[PDB]
Amino acid sequence: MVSLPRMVYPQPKVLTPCRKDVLVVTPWLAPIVWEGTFNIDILNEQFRLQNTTIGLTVFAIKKYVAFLKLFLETAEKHFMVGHRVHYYVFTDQPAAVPRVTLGTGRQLSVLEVCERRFLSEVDYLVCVDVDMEFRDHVGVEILTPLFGTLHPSFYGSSREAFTYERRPQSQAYIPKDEGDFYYMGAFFGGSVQEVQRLTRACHQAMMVDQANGIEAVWHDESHLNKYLLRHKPTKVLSPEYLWDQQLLGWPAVLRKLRFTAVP
Ligand SMILES: CCCCCCCCO[C@@H]1O[C@H](CO)[C@H](O)[C@H](N)[C@H]1O[C@@H]1O[C@@H](C)[C@@H](O)[C@@H](O)[C@@H]1O
Ligand SMILES: [Hg+2]
Ligand SMILES: [Hg+2]
């Protein structure tokens, strides 16, 4: 909206790609976010000028409350640092939420287990699993109306290998000749409006499956994939954003490991 200030940085080279080893844009022209494809200083300026507020939602029920301390502590070091952040922790154990020290402009709300609240408190919603930890920068480069993240086990696989729901009787059904990528349900987001549209669509699809006595092979994630196939995400995050170094190591194609599973 408002003009950017004078900035000094390397000139982009039209005849020189940032990454030649990976696909950096989808066939529907959505950027695929990899290290080396973005100048974070320009993006930080753009989003700060809009006073962007990012909501980060996590569910922590039963034994999963034990993962909150590390999750939040590392989020404080790597997630949207410099921007307004509102954590939303949905849990069945409010008193079990650890007291983590937050940086300025960041807040945390504990919700024991309306959506209109999100529309009035944040601009973007980022939905992730709690048994994870941030190990490197996860910032505004991910913000867009709707984004999904490439599952680390299938980013180099053929669509036939994708573990989509293959039974026509399920609303999440995707035939062998269809599919762009296999997105992991552990990290997705977008504007509040788009995220709520996705969740409402997923919820209705799962209810229909329940009525027909069928459960998608990978539950919510199967429906997430059906939704993103029919409603293309405006940005796709590379596996840098969802990794497990113990199970997958550290491939050369991954310059940074940003958000990983906890052993
Ligand atoms: C963010 C690190 C994930 C690394 C990948 C491990 C491979 C098994 O992943 C499972 O993949 C299926 C799809 O085929 C579903 O996406 C499952 N939800 C995935 O399970 C995850 O990973 C396993 C190892 C375990 O930690 C589960 O709790 C977790 O949900
Ligand atoms: Hg969410
Ligand atoms: Hg979903």
Image (tube, rainbow, N blue to C red):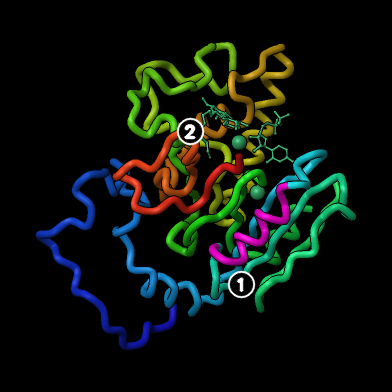
As drawn, is 74 to the left or to the right of 12? Answer: right
As drawn, is 105 to the left or to the right of 113? Answer: left
Q: Which residue is mark 1?
A: 84
Residue 101 on image: x %, y %? 73, 70
Q: Does residue 167 appear in the picture of this structure?
A: yes
The vertical placement of 58 against 175, above or below, is: below
As drawn, is 32 to the left or to the right of 226? Answer: left
Q: Residues within 10 Å of mark 1 (few under 14, many from 20)?
A: some
As drawn, is 126 to the left or to the right of 179? Answer: right
Q: Nearer the viewer, residue 220 or 203?
A: 220
Q: Is residue 115 magenta?
A: no
- The segment highlighted magenta reads 67-78
Residue 38 on image: x %, y %? 33, 63
Q: Nearer the viewer, residue 5 or 67?
A: 67
Kind of residue sitting beneath label 1:
Arg
Q: Where on the picture, by quarter, is residue 95?
A: bottom right
Q: Which residue is mark 2?
A: 247
Residue 116 on image: x %, y %? 74, 57
Instruction: Please tell me which residue is depicted at 64% across the width and 41% down the height of the picture.
Output: 199
Residue 249 on image: x %, y %? 41, 38
Magenta stretch prevailing secondary structure: helix
